[PDB]
Image (tube, rainbow over all chains, first blue to last red; front, side, top):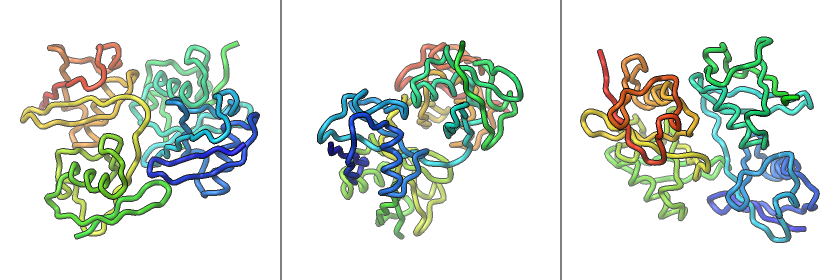
Length: 149
Length: 149
């Protein structure tokens, strides 16, 4: 099926897709066609930011559906949140951001409830009320992300 | 004097301006050329989101400087911070951001050290560690900034 991805300037990317294709697959196509890194890409449909792990069918995206592409600026501090599946999530953050706030971003991006998230850094399970600075988390530091068992 | 406004797809818009032109006036020009409503526009320069009620000269924007045009956001909410002169600081923020983080953002936008900042909302001094939601701070709430030597 054919779908359209539009920037908020009206710049359009037309994609050949399958209902079982994932949002991550779509970002890969956008990178190959437009040269936009997947990390900068934010896809929106029906007012929701679309999670990489989900399929187009999961979001009820169908023939001739129009998705919105919002792009994230780099700017200052980035950190990596890394799964043991080998997925590396880039987050734009600030030193005074709390772990609670980071998990809220992960919930938005990946659909994981904050209470199910375990972030690990320096061998420690990170607590929600502390800042990145409190934990000495620096530019391009990596946090391990695993689920509660 | 001309300036550039660039989207993250690389589309560049060239504007005629004077140094006393306001950010609001720049957004209006962007709407005239691109059709993007000012409220969805976010202009980034020197690592800061630019305030509508300020001039180009206020930000040391010079001939053929480039501004980043980030579109809509998506995301959370705007709050206002009133200075002693009645001057408004507009911040993009999330419910789980802490007061400590709000002070950090004020530093980023105004160059005021966090240790010299006190924030007040509904007649109370706000603790650094608590979140905006914890203080019942919602969309377009106005905070008061009080500074100390």
